[PDB]
Amino acid sequence: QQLTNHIRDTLPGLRNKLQSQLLSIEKEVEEYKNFRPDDPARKTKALLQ
Amino acid sequence: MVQQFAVDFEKRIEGSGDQIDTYELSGGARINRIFHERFPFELVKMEFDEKELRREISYAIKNIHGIRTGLFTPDMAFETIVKKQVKKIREPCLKCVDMVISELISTVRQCTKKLQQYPRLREEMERIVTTHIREREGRTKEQVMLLIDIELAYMNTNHEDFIGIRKGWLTINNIGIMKGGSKEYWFVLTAENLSWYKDDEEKEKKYMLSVDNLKLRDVEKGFMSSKHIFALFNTEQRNVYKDYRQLELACETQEEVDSWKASFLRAGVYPEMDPQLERQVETIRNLVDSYMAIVNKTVRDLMPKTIMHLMINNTKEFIFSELLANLYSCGDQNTLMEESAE
């Protein structure tokens, strides 16, 4: 019972770490997931930036 | 044009660059520094009648002591007055946010309608920016509320609170026959004691008197009627410690006499419950003012910082990084960038 209580008590720490990593990465994968080689608009946006 | 818009907006609101409008206006988003120096006005537009504050404090004490006899002023009599005063500033903070949003919308319009000849483009580039501004209105208001709510959550008396009232010159007209004449001196009246000085350095400390157990009266016209006169007299002892014929004191006007009397009344003196409660009420009133000065100071400082972080900087980041991505998403990209007849 103590081993089970310990293993469950650490879940909140792991959940916050994974949630933090998704928030940091999300801003860029949102754009990478929409990559298409045939996209003159993507090229134009990069040029302006 | 997108490049020119982003650059023009940033110059106008930050104030950087050349070609500044040195003559015509105080304008171009430098108006916002007025709100940050106008919001300090709304925080003092509010007023209260002190008699309502005294009544409210009195019921606060009696309602904290439910049945018990009171020895010391309860702390909750302080906390529940401060919480009630702080709730009042929710409104002016929201007015400040709304005024700032209004100026951002006006500035976006100047940088858009006046510089672009293409139809439809000046609509998309105005619509998108004002939509983004409105969403930040939402996030900004939540943060302001979670700041005032924090001011209520805990009372901190460590930094600048009053850590544990009237001044002017008076002349004594009736001097003992061994000296004669009249003596002009510096008088300091506090809520606790009276102190006599020879000058405004307040170094001599020649006389000290208690405020308690003294009485005030007017004087009969047995004198050359050139000054207004009152008397501070004692009925519990034959002398006012160091006495000068019941300390008859002349003033230039009756209004000065009445202001003095009012100051004595504030200090605890009675006119020509009462023993215990009135002293407790005055202690709380003073402590409340000293703490509210700190609350107001902190609010004036943090509000413009909250707005800059949450509304202004995110708008600039949007203009530089996202604006073009959204214009490609509007309409059908066929009627956009179609020349007007002119």
Image (tube, grey):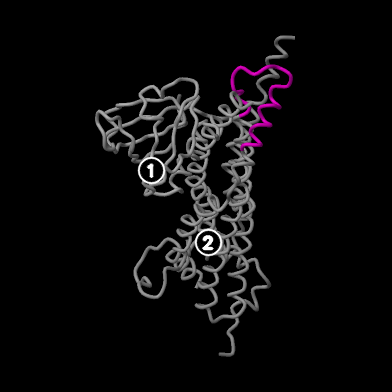
x 66%, y 69%: residue = B330
Q: Nearer the viewer, mark 2 or mark 1?
A: 1
- Magenta segment, which residues? B54-77
Residue B192 image-quadrant placement: top left
Mark 2 or mark 1, earlier in chain: 1
Tell me, for residue B319, which label it has, or none.
2
The extreme top residue here reads: A2
Q: What crowding class fits label 1: few (fewer than 14 Cα within 10 Å), some (14-19), or many (20 or more)?
A: few
Callout 1: residue from which chain?
B
Q: Position of residue B225 (x, y in %)?
A: 39, 48
**Amino acid carrying mark 2 in the image:** Ile
**Amino acid carrying mark 1 in the image:** Phe
Label 1: state its secondary structure. loop
Q: Position of residue B31 (x, y in %)?
A: 47, 63
Tell me, for residue B126, which label it has, or none.
none
What residue is pinned by disc 1? Answer: B223
Residue B198 image-quadrant placement: top left
Q: Is residue B179 above or below residue B307?
A: above
